[PDB]
Length: 263
Ligand SMILES: CO[C@@]1(c2cccc(-c3cn(C)c4cnc(NC(N)=O)cc34)n2)CCOC1
Image 1 (cartoon, rainbow, N blue to C red):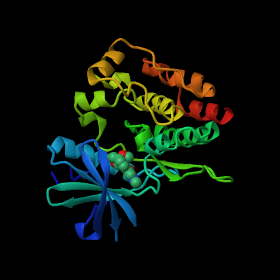
Image 2 (image 1 turned 90 degrees about the vertical axis):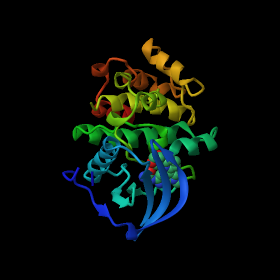
Image 3 (image 1 turned 120 degrees about the vertical axis):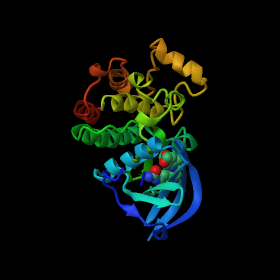
């Protein structure tokens, strides 16, 4: 343990202060903190080496990319038996939580801005041949709200947490319909994730299949059922192209981004 062949900044525990609990991610508890910067501390549960390795791989890869719409990763701290990823605090938190609270008065124009910013971030990851693997409204963080007159939203995509490759079948099923179908048993999976996230954003933060059970979610992919049409009709062609069960038929993010700018 503590791989020694990945590149990430090692944060000393004397440099971080842990403040309030914010929520949970997959096998993590996340806390507001300070880095002597306003940060978020993502404390991994006591885990087997394989899970910790997938956590450190995310930290290393997200430490070496840069983009206007990607949240910073500052490093990893080992505080006793706890691996803690130190990441950027994004002022207004997860998009899906805010959208549900503000449901009914978030205009379509606002959602198209967000879609375009997200597509831009994924276009960059595609060009670098890097998989995110956890594109969803929860992992879209709002840096600027953009509802007030003369303003516009600004989002940052959070890190994917513990790498998808290390997660259990039951955790993968919990991620339906954001999870690409081929992942239930490549950067193409993030096209599906993006498409599902557009449905979520259009539905003001309510994802399709939310009221279903794990077994029913798994059934949905098993029988290759069709996901719903978005409530922004101008996105219906785009979402249908991304939410295709065959991965090679999904369009590239260069095409997605171009199409969004014309919509
Ligand atoms: C987005 O999923 C996580 C999560 C869950 C619930 C709340 C927040 C969350 C609430 N607030 C106010 C934040 C401010 N900044 C960030 N920053 C970064 N880099 O995620 C996250 C949050 N995060 C779970 C896995 O990781 C974070």
